[PDB]
Image 1 (cartoon, each protein chain N blue to C red):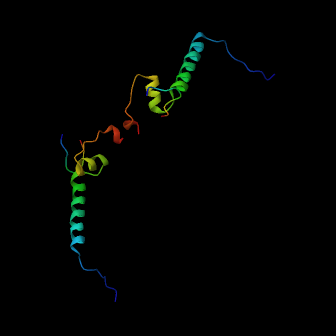
Image 2: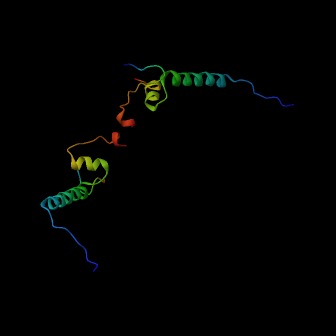
Image 3: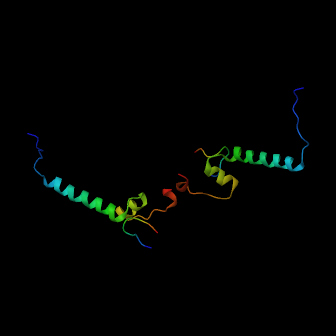
Amino acid sequence: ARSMRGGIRL
Amino acid sequence: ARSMRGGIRL
Amino acid sequence: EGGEVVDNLTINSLRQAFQLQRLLERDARGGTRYIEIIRSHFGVISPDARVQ
Amino acid sequence: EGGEVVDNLTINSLRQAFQLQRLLERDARGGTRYIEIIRSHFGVISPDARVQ
């Protein structure tokens, strides 16, 4: 639910 | 400052 | 020869003509930018930022 | 004949190369959609609606 590595993908 | 006739123009 | 034939008027056609005229009068009076349409045809105050 | 000539390295060139690499690493790690750039390079949580 936070800022993931590699940009957002759900 | 309300909804004018003829649409918005300032 | 060379006339124009039109059918009998239904009350449904006639009330549709009235409500179409009300729609075009609301567009003239209210404005036609997409934000003006929303504010005139519905109760809604859209933010400017989300409509570009 | 047919070599490649490069000038002496200034410390200003060298620190600019380091900070450029930090920027490209932040882009890889953080993402590169415009909302991901804003959230990774600045403290800012933009609404999705205003960025289309």
